[PDB]
Image: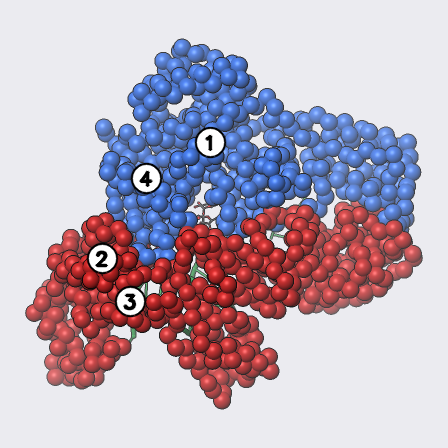
Chain colours: A red, B blue, C green
DNA sequence: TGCCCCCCCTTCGGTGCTTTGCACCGAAGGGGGGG
């Protein structure tokens, strides 16, 4: 049926008119699919015949529903969508089963022909004009317009969800201890009533939906576990993902690897330890989706590791609001982190991973802090609170980081957990110059227009060096000059530069970088005992710096 | 009443900013608050055909246990028409910063007695989120002058002055400044006699519909140079770099006769004696750094900018300026929250006190340059916010080339 | 040959800097998943 809910007023964008796009050819199996849908949507009043005074059109097609023996009608409203007003979408996220409480009685219902039970603004219907082909050659076609929400229109999902929300609200208020998870036309209904009273409330919910035109076919009325919901399986005490099948291939195209990583990312919500760094490395610098990419040795290993993890059966548990949330993080290498969120040990609510490189130069402590921030946000979304953290970093390491890093940084309540590899600072610059250490005055200049430069140093022990550099930059020659001083110095060194840029990077104490040259500087910094790094202004005649700047020019 | 016609600035559209996640206790409060406002007609339930949105969250003061709804209308206020162009702005009184004590009162509720132009209401939409996205968001828009909107003090202008004019006659030497939803009221009365005419002011207001500031101890911290008996090459290098930067701010500061103390390729720890002409140069530079800079005046047509630096051990330096190197105010914020541990809390508190000082002194908040990663700030700042206003800010990572402000 | 949402990984183009490349950021392209 068609809901008697008031329609939602909708506009085209200012200046714009309607679509005018001739129809294309379809199979006979799909023409008879739609004529059966379309003379029958007309009898129930979902569409109406029109003709030549309405100048608009938009092409139409059908795909097979995932239930087989049923077809989904779709119109290619790409043109109308562009000239239709913007909407504020009210679907703000996706419910997750780790946010659910244990319930004594559970039911899953789905509304039938959801979109077609919601009417469309009277004044907007004429822009939904289309035509049914019937073998193209035999007849020009029959023109209709939508009286209800069409599948493929930009505004249909939001107008349905908002309509469903208004219809549900009387029932929610009248029944505050029945949880209704509402995603599109899919309703999860849990309660702590014995199944008798529960099914009374269920049939009363369905009858309330029916008065407002929303059927709930028995076909999609789940009454017993395991419930199929949002891609998962809900058992009474636990939940699982529906089975994940990864591609297996002799030869891999870029698109195959793209699909592989996406599935692994989906699996990572419950399968701990998933890694995709080396498989995704294969997608860089590629230029086509059909390009055959051979797997590197490292990608084969990573895929094999994931395949071992996935052959194991896993489950999540549900949320107990009387117990604390606990998040534990482990380091995996190459900027990869994996985490589990639980309340009782060895009983995961869910898992996840963090593996983004923010910045050209960073360190493990920064990335641990980012992983904490992602977990904190995800916990607010799912449970409305942040968890207590268990982290593989020691209090002294963190304390040394937030006193010598100049940016404000923080991490909540956390308990140190000894799960190597531990997160650590890989070097620390001295706060003061070092007695007995050699002093290097470093400098490098480059020619903006020529690409050619030089890096070099002068030394309080009389040492000097200049290396010529080609196809370089100003900032590179300054980094290179610091590279030389670290290369030719002993275990303890004092370095004076005039590049704020180079000071900025190194003083942040990075341990990884997208720059090979910065990576070289980092490996040298880690092998040293003590390093004091000092800045001076250039071209003000200051001893050491002036002499080296002479030598580089 | 009659609405006042309101416009966005030419060629600008309304705000389109996504709601961010909220805790359980903040969502419940917003649901409690907004259902009451809907019942009183102050807001209306809307749907997705309104394409605008503004984030909403909630704050609770340490002293005031009740939750306060806070709509982040920064985007909308930027796009709203000027009201100084239409002559309905609020003049700032110079005397407020002179007063012994200033108390801040939240009078945003008075706005809810005046309706908003029906054609402007759609720009005020906001969306309450759902825990675990159990439901779609719930959308409202205002029917009255919104709290946090810069047009509300301007439209309510004529009315607030008439509510306040008996108090203003009765008490000539107390000065009252409206800024957004806040009344900043200052006087010279005793530390606790001042508080009682606060309470009389509030009853007169409660008739129709924070903590005590103390400006005469908002001391400036100048640039100061180290004092030692002995100086290493590194000390002189750092001191020459510190004054070479400061010469962009001050006039006639010189390094020529400390620089050549370092002629030659010297070790960083070698102790160089001080010439008489280097003590000449230093003791004098101490004096230019002593007293403030000549030629620096506030311009109300230009923006205020604020820079902050973490210095450690709980302390935070800041500078407020409009043109670079012409500081209207230099300062040092110190915490005493207890444990010394939380950088984000200290910086959030520092921003509120610095912005409070600009309101008292100049009448508007500065645009902050914050020494913090964007996503570290956004993970935590609403936890510590206590003001009904929100300043504009941006995120910088400037390493300290020199420790200029210590 | 459709629509809306969330997630991750990669690429690209805009912005500001007392710059001449560099680092940051948001959008857009692919993938996963949901209805
Ligand atoms: N590929 C898809 C799947 C779903 N939907 C939207 C329109 C649907 O009406 C609604 C609900 O999805 P369903 O699978 O439940 O389809 P229907 O409710 O329309 O029909 P049925 O009775 O088979 O459930 O979500 C869509 O636009 N495109
Ligand atoms: O923190 C920046 C972040 O906040 C948003 C809103 O969530 O923008 C707000 O803050 C900006 C900085 O002051 C303002 O310019 C803007 O008007 C205000 O809405 C996001 O847009 C932005 O990513
Ligand atoms: Mg359905």
Q: Nearer the viewer, mark 4 or mark 3?
A: 4
Residue picked out by circle 2? A164
Secondary element under disc 1, as helix, strand or loop, is: loop
Disc 2 is attached to a residue of which chain? A
Q: Are marks 3 and 2 on the same chain?
A: yes
Disc 4: which residue? B33
Work out how far the residue at label 4 is from the one at label 2, CA to CA, in angstroms. 24 Å
Would residue B28 be seen by someone viewing this image from the given angle?
A: yes
The residue beneath circle 1 is B63
Cα separation between marks 4 and 3: 41 Å
> Total number of numbered labels?
4
Residue position marked by numbered label 3 in the rendering: A78
Residue A339 appears left or right of A487: left
Image-quadrant location for residue A34: bottom left
Vertical comparison of B205 with A255: above or below? above
Q: Nearer the viewer, mark 3 or mark 2?
A: 2
Give the crowd class for mark 3: few <14, some 14-19, many >=20 residues within 10 Å: some
* Marks 1 and 4 on same chain: yes
Marks 3 and 2, how far apart in space?
25 Å
* Dot 3 and dot 1 within a common chain: no
Is residue B150 positioned above or below A313 on the image?
A: above
Q: Is residue A384 left or right of residue A124?
A: right
Viewer-proximal residue among A115 and A391 = A391
- Residue in the image at 54% along x and 81% along y: A304
The front one of B206 and A153 is B206
């Amino acid at each position: 049926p068609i809901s008697p809910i008031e329609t939602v007023p909708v506009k085209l964008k200012p200046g714009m008119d309607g679509p005018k796009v001739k129809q294309w050819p379809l199979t006979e199996e799909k023409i008879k699919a739609l004529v059966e849908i379309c003379t029958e949507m007309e009898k129930e009043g979902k569409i109406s015949k029109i003709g030549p005074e309405n100048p608009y059109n938009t092409p139409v097609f059908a795909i097979k529903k995932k239930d087989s023996t049923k077809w989904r009608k779709l119109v290619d409203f790409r043109e109308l969508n562009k000239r239709t007003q913007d909407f504020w979408e009210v679907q703000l996220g996706i419910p997750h089963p780790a946010g659910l409480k244990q319930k004594k009685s559970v039911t899953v219902l789905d509304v039938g022909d959801a979109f077609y039970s919601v009417p469309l603004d009277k004044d907007f219907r004429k822009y939904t004009a289309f035509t049914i082909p019937s073998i193209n050659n035999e007849t020009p076609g029959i023109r209709y317009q939508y009286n209800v929400l069409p599948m493929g229109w930009k505004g249909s999902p939001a107008i349905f969800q908002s309509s469903m929300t208004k219809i549900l609200e009387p029932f929610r208020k009248q029944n505050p201890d029945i949880v209704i998870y509402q995603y599109m036309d899919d309703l999860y209904v849990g309660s702590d009533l014995e199944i008798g009273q529960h099914r009374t409330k269920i049939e009363e919910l369905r009858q309330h939906l029916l008065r407002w035109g929303f059927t709930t076919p028995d076909k999609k009325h789940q009454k017993e576990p395991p419930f199929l919901w949002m891609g998962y399986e809900l058992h009474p005490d636990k939940w699982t993902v529906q089975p994940i099948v990864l591609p297996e291939k002799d030869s891999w195209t870029v698109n195959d690897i793209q699909k592989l990583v996406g599935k692994l990312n989906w699996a990572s919500q419950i399968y701990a330890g998933i890694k995709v760094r080396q498989l995704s490395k294969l997608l860089r610098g590629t230029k086509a989706l059909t390009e055959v990419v051979p797997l590197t040795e490292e990608a084969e290993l990573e895929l094999a590791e994931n395949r071992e993890i996935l052959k194991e059966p896993v489950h999540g548990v549900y949320y107990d609001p009387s117990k604390d949330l606990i998040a534990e993080i482990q380091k995996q290498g190459q900027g990869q982190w994996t985490y589990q969120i639980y309340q009782e040990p060895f009983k995961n609510l869910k898992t996840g991973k963090y593996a983004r490189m923010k910045g050209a130069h960073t360190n493990d402590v920064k990335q641990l802090t980012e992983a904490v921030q992602k977990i904190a946000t995800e916990s607010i979304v799912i449970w409305g609170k942040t968890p207590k953290f268990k982290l593989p970093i020691q209090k002294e390491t963190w304390e040394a980081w937030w006193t010598e890093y100049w940016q404000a940084t923080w991490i909540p309540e956390w308990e140190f957990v000894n799960t190597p590899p531990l997160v650590k600072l890989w070097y620390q610059l001295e706060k003061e110059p070092i007695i007995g250490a050699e002093t290097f005055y470093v400098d490098g200049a480059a020619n903006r227009e020529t690409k050619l430069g030089k890096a070099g140093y002068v030394t309080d022990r009389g040492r000097q060096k200049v290396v010529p550099l080609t196809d370089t930059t100003n900032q590179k020659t300054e980094l290179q000059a610091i590279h030389l001083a670290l290369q030719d110095s002993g275990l303890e060194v004092n370095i004076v530069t005039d590049s704020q840029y180079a000071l900025g990077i190194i003083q942040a104490q990075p341990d990884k970088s997208e720059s090979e040259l910065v990576s070289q500087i980092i490996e040298q910094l880690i092998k040293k005992e003590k390093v004091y790094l000092a800045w001076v202004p250039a071209h003000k005649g200051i001893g050491g710096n002036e002499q080296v700047d002479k030598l580089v020019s | 009443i009659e609405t006042v016609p309101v416009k966005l600035k030419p060629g600008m559209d309304g705000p389109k900013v996504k709601q961010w996640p909220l805790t359980e206790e903040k969502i419940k409060a917003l649901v409690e608050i907004c259902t009451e406002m809907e019942k009183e007609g102050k807001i209306s339930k809307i749907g997705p055909e309104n394409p605008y949105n503004t984030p909403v969250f909630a704050i609770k003061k340490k002293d005031s246990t009740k939750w306060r709804k806070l709509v982040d209308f920064r985007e909308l206020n930027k796009r709203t028409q000027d009201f100084w162009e239409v002559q309905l702005g609020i003049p700032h009184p110079a005397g407020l910063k002179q007063k012994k004590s200033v108390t801040v009162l939240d009078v945003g509720d008075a706005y809810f007695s005046v309706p908003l132009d029906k054609d402007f209401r759609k720009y005020t939409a906001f969306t309450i989120p759902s825990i675990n996205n159990e439901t779609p968001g719930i959308r409202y828009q205002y029917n009255v002058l919104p709290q946090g909107w810069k047009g509300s003090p301007a439209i309510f202008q004529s009315s607030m002055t008439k509510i306040l004019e008996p108090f203003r006659k009765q008490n000539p030497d107390i000065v009252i400044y409206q800024y957004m939803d806040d009344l900043y009221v200052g006087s010279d009365l005793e530390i606790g006699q001042h508080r009682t005419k606060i309470e009389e002011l509030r009853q007169h207001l409660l008739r129709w519909g924070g903590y005590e500031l103390h400006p005469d101890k908002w001391t400036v911290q100048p640039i100061v140079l180290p004092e030692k008996d002995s100086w290493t090459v590194n000390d002189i290098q750092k001191l020459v770099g510190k004054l070479n930067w400061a010469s962009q701010i001050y006039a006639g500061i010189k390094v020529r006769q400390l620089s050549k103390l370092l002629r030659g390729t010297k070790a960083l720890t070698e102790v160089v004696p001080l010439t008489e002409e280097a003590e000449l140069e230093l003791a004098e530079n101490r004096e230019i750094l002593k007293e403030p800079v000549h030629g620096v005046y506030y311009d109300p047509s230009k923006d205020l900018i604020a820079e902050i630096q973490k210095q450690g051990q709980g302390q935070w330096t800041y500078q407020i300026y409009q043109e670079p190197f012409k500081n209207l105010k230099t300062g040092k914020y110190a915490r005493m929250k207890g444990a010394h541990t939380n950088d984000v809390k200290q910086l959030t508190e520092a921003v509120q006190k610095i912005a409070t000082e600009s309101i008292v002194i100049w009448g508007k908040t500065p645009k902050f340059k914050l020494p913090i990663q964007k996503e570290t700030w956004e993970a935590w700042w609403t936890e510590y916010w206590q003001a009904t206003w929100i300043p504009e800010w941006e995120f910088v990572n400037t390493p300290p080339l020199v420790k200029l402000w210590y």
